[PDB]
Length: 94
Image (tube, rainbow, N blue to C red; front, side):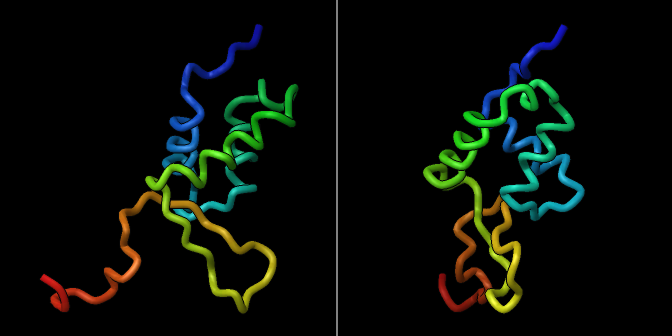
């Protein structure tokens, strides 16, 4: 018998980052984690994969930190962070 995870789609995205060997994980990498942790999704591939991407955009809780554009191939990472866009410098603003 198989049972789906009572975890909501948003919670699954949150758990994947926590159990991700690397805090920065690609969108494609997140799908692989769910397939192994929960095999019920393997029976149904199309449908749930797209919904996760839809949330990974409207929700501002997640922060996208792409690698340098010079390196091709993968170009997207997911991690938990605030609006740390220019927080690189401190003391410049009060």
